[PDB]
Length: 446
Ligand SMILES: Cc1cc(F)c2[nH]c(=O)n(C3CCN(C4CCOCC4)CC3)c2c1
Ligand SMILES: CCCCCCCC/C=C/CCCCCCCC(=O)O
Ligand SMILES: CCCCCCCC/C=C\CCCCCCCC(=O)O
Ligand SMILES: CCCCCCCC/C=C\CCCCCCCC(=O)O
Ligand SMILES: CCCCCCCC/C=C\CCCCCCCC(=O)O
Ligand SMILES: CCCCCCCC/C=C\CCCCCCCC(=O)O
Image (cartoon, rainbow, N blue to C red; front, side):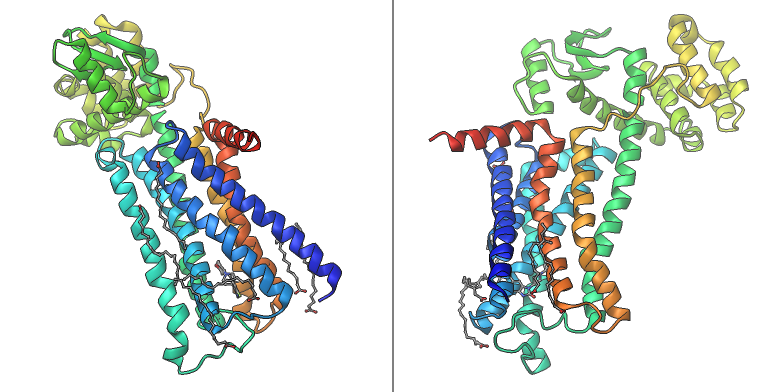
């Protein structure tokens, strides 16, 4: 190729590599230097940054030299090893995105059961298996295909994957590395968004009715409580309540906690309440029949009265499962509950009557940094890997239709995912953005 083309491509690919190596190092150092970033989900982000660092420093630079030189000069053994390192790191990134998606899925859908298992030790176990599965699946086929076929069909001065020669096998790998992971992650995201907004509404409902307290207080029984009726301990000690609070959050709070930390505790209490409802033979048929809004009004009653208290409304529960909401509203209002808390009872009864949030006046979806990051890193994956996967799709129906140049650009677009991944964290998380700025200004300072 021309000397002018060699300089132009080397500069663009070089600057892209520099942006990839810098961004993923900044992401890794951020989790290392900042304690507030040292969360179980950020262990997977560190693992993803490791895969993206190989892509930036090794894959990108070595693939660009291969295109510029127009041939492979390092030999057949260096070639297959280079391709093995490349494919395993690229798949490890996809596996890490699946780990981020599943962790976010189980922590939102199951805040009680899953957070018993959500320790850093289990995150490290899942990270290692993800990297090991990527290796066991792609490296043996990359290196030993030539021995199983009986010949190395890749010429000297050429470096490419031998088993990806036929377009149907390329499509097979595309299904396993793109089409199936994307489908799985999208289905997981629709469930995470629906669950998050559903739980938020229960949180905002009880914030109006029961009340939210950021500091440790004593309940009616005299036990230390926090947030929306979250029991810390039954022990008559302030320090014991503080120790149990620091255990539940993971930091030295010393009495005071944030709204988001109180929401985390409340969602464990919602899971504990729903566990009791399904285990109660008198509350299970009505709960299964009610919609998301009317289920929350039943949970509201469980948080105030208790399991057996709501079960006392034999007449009312029967009319709610029969979808006769005007009838059940009359029986619910004619009780000791309505007389004790008239303002709260009317709001809950109206919720059962209408099946809407008109009694409370609710705000739109508060898209938390974690939800925004997941959506950004998933869209980043779809955007950068779509060109190559469309080329694979047209390759199956069109033999040798895709030119050498297009494959080279489609390969380079897949690597751009590694460049834009730390940008997604910076754009969605304020704690990452500030640490990125902090580390960059600290590096410029000698
Ligand atoms: C480092 C290196 C050196 C070379 F000489 C290469 N030759 C060659 O064809 N590649 C490909 C580059 C793209 N990569 C993708 C495939 C889709 O999944 C994400 C990774 C597969 C190997 C080479 C890579
Ligand atoms: C086991 C891990 C795999 C890594 C080992 C593969 C060998 C890679 C060697 C890289 C040396 C860099 C030389 C740069 C010139 C490239 C010239 C070319 O081949 O076109
Ligand atoms: C050729 C080089 C390949 C190296 C890949 C190694 C596999 C990556 C392993 C995972 C890194 C561990 C992630 C957890 C770090 C915790 C960060 C912290 O909070 O201190
Ligand atoms: C775990 C780290 C291992 C990485 C070591 C990399 C060493 C690669 C060395 C060069 C291999 C060249 C061997 C000659 C192959 C034949 C060349 C040809 O087909 O023209
Ligand atoms: C021959 C190709 C060479 C490529 C080497 C890089 C590929 C990574 C391979 C698998 C190692 C598995 C990583 C396990 C480390 C555990 C890290 C942790 O979770 O703390
Ligand atoms: C950031 C954007 C910059 C993009 C840089 C990459 C530019 C590469 C573009 C393609 C030029 C095409 C090269 C000519 C190949 C001819 C092969 C043929 O005739 O089939």
